[PDB]
Image (cartoon, rainbow over the protein chains, first blue to last red):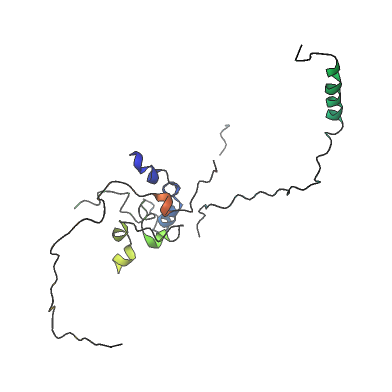
Length: 36
Length: 49
Length: 49
Length: 49
């Protein structure tokens, strides 16, 4: 696994905002006071 | 249109060094304290004794 | 004849779809000169065409 | 200069190629994985250190 350090800890794998961006485009299916 | 971060150059604004950009006194108080630390060495150890 | 075998390389929004699709990789900062051996399996706009 | 023009004289495929003989391997056929920071030279971490 260690030679893949050049691939594993790259920041673009830890950026889900494009994944969330293309996940928003498909249709979404449908199927506070802590004291008191 | 997405907020990706990129490597910007390290910018920090400073003052370019000159021949007369003078450092001032330490508000006259540590000036006096350094004066006392100077004059207390007349009586004390001598490091060759 | 299952649905898929690997849901991190097959969805519309999987990890590789934002990583290896060169139409999607252009939105990120990337070097075009580096040949990627897997771009032929993901660049779906050519595959749709 | 000598401008030529060719026009095919067959209704179908009149010519057949085939992969005949392999001399050597240009690549290493190795496991040395490529580097993502080289192919993505712009993306950084949000924290600096």
